[PDB]
Image (spheres, rainbow, N blue to C red):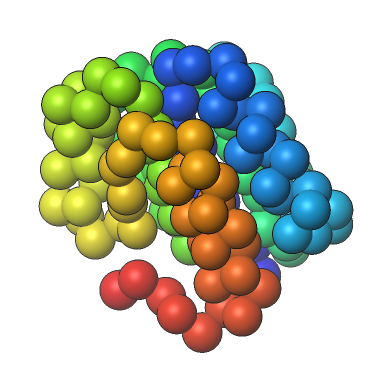
Amino acid sequence: MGTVVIVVSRDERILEELLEVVLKSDPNVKTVRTDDKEKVKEEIEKARKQGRPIVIFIRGATEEVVRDIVEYAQKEGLRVLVIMVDQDQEELERIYEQLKKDGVDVRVTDNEDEAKKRLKELLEKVLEHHHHHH
């Protein structure tokens, strides 16, 4: 159908571990790492043309980056699953409250292992495609 997973981490080593999780879960899921928020949108449309899931990886995505990409994926009619993992948690909670307000699937934590567990967890909800958040 088409499904977008927004991964926001401000630490390098988190993005690559979460990429590893997508590859070990399923390689056919489209994976993207551009921190250019417009270039993300280009690859969102491409994934909708492929009619498949896509996992976006951005280093240091501030609130106005994340909300801007999430609402765009919703314009396309795609299901949005958002992981935000970094030690600047209160910052990620302002992103969280903005997206949660809409009813977007969101989660915030700061832990390598937890991030990687909940990464595969989302990918399994997407392949199953039964558990839509709202």
